[PDB]
Image (cartoon, helix red, strand yellow):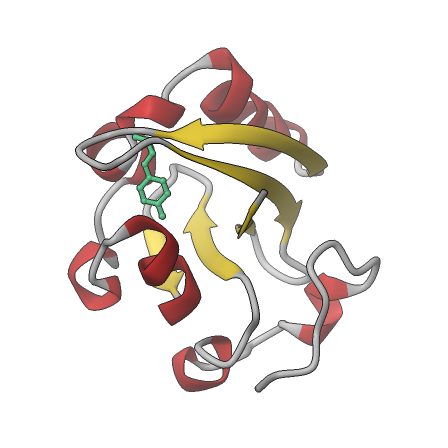
Length: 125
Ligand SMILES: *C(=O)/C=C/c1ccc(O)cc1
């Protein structure tokens, strides 16, 4: 696979500029968002967790379109606050339940190293 653990302290360095192929080798779901929440990258593990087809969701807005169950203070609010501050590093459990069997996950959102983009990492719990 790719040898990176969920929640690693330097994950943003390890995944910096990772192409879509390499991202598909992670053991956990990985989504890269711009500051508005548009999907830039979406890996295979995430698609397995959620059922979404990665290439279909890239370019969509995660909060508006793909994941309305995350359009809440508890998820989007945290994301939006992090984007506004230009800093984000949070881990929390959540349940994904839009047009899918409800699935509890652990989420790690972390600002990407460079630029202004934001990772959403997901694993099952
Ligand atoms: C709630 O609507 C959650 C949906 C969802 C979460 C994560 C994804 O990668 C895709 C859909």
